[PDB]
Amino acid sequence: FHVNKSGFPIDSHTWERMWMHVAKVHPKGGEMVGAIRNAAFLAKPSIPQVPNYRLSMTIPDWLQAIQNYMKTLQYNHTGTQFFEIRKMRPLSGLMETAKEMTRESLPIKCLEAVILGIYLTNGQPSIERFPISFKTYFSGNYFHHVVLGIYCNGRYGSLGMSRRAELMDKPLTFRTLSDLIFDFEDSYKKYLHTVKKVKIGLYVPHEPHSFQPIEWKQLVLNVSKMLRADIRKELEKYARDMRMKILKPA
Amino acid sequence: QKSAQQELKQRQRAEIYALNRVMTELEQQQFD
Image (cartoon, rainbow over all chains, first blue to last red; front, side, top):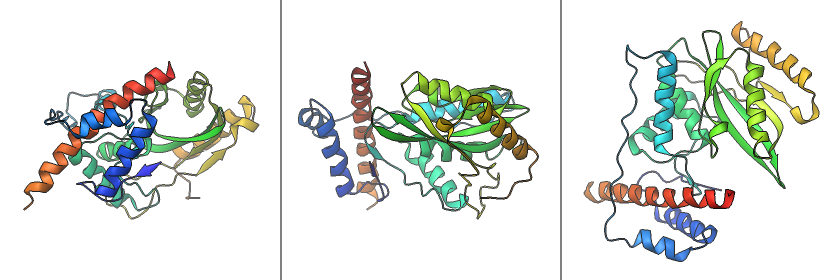
């Protein structure tokens, strides 16, 4: 609901709004907040080392290394996203926000994880990266979510962060893009979410100093109004276009 | 000078991570 636009050491208006929020949602509320803010001393949390690609890792080892870093930073349940991602900025600035994430070492949410995943795979030219975004219905309201689709040596997979383990990373085992999307769909089924809309971007450039932004909306499918066979038809058509490397941004 | 800013970043980190644990344990009681 709230996003930190004030840098690091978080300003006071943003700080108070974080706590004020969490005192409402929590049942223990004002007591649980009092216990943290007023604690005489608190343990400094360990700082995970930023993962480094070694000659002894396979591409699956590397993606698991990156993903484990993300799991260690932890998903952010505080209600205040700590790094501002302006989705439509050139990669170069997003890349700098990613560096800042590895320096400040705070919890991250879905969109921050995608930016950080691009950053940590920029040095592996055989890994292609494209965003995957979902719009979902659950019991009243709509929800948005994004992960980082991965394509490498004829297989698809993903990196990401989510409240649920089944809507983040997927091992590089899916032989088609349709198979991966349908696995997210069935993962969402387990939490009573109906997938309304699926959005797929283009491969992201590997140059960390690119002026061009991320294309998030190359293919857009209202899968709730579609039967399985027509979704697969269009994804395979689009996935063929990605790999043939012919497409111009939308 | 840059003394109080680095101590403040460090306490805010510790506070954020304290809070993140209690929020994570909360969101599972609700989910269950």
